[PDB]
Amino acid sequence: AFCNLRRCELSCRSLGLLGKCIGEECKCVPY
């Protein structure tokens, strides 16, 4: 599915990660 990525990606990008959608919720990893 898609994710509520407006929660994660604008907080994960500062470490040089991306916000990745894990079916229906976000985790973060580079890159």
Image (tube, rainbow, N blue to C red):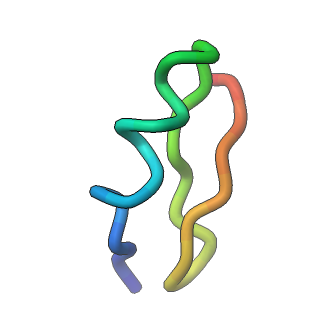
Residue 19 pos. (x, y %): 51, 45
Question: Disc count in the image?
Answer: 0
Question: Residue 26, position in %: x, y?
Answer: 56, 65
Viewed as shown, does residue 12 lie left or right of 31?
A: left
Vertical order, 10 against 16 (above or below): below
Q: Please identify the quarter of the rendering in which residue 7 is found.
A: bottom left
Please provide percent x and percent y for residue 13.
47, 24
Identify the image quadrant of the C terminus: top right
Quadrant location of residue 2?
bottom left
Residue at figure coordinates x 71%, y 36% from the top left: 29
Q: Residue at x 38, y 74 (%)?
A: 3
Residue at (63, 16) in percent of width and height? 15
Foreground residue, 1 or 26? 26
Left/right placement of residue 8 relative to residue 16 reads left
Vertical placement of residue 16 versus 22, above or below: above
Which quadrant of the figure contains the N terminus? bottom left
Q: Is residue 24 above or below residue 7?
A: below
Residue 19 in the image: above or below residue 21: above
